[PDB]
Image 1 (cartoon, rainbow over the protein chains, first blue to last red):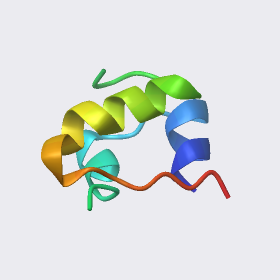
Image 2 (tube, each protein chain N blue to C red):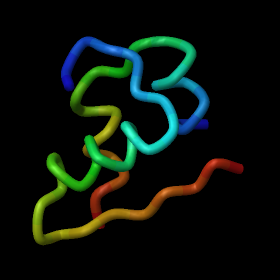
Image 3 (cartoon, helix red, strand yellow):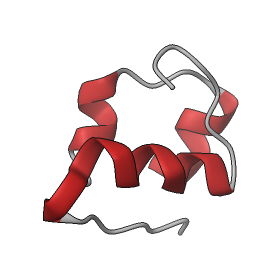
Image 4 (cartoon, rainbow over the protein chains, first blue to last red):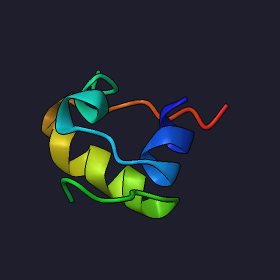
Length: 21
Length: 29
């Protein structure tokens, strides 16, 4: 998932912002 | 914190900054 991907690879900002409420 | 590896607490710090007063959910699963 996200916790994995953004650590092992590089996430774009919009991938992060998908987890805002 | 754009264009970098965000591991452990650093991902949470990034989410806090991005999401602001919306808050966010964090699910390592």
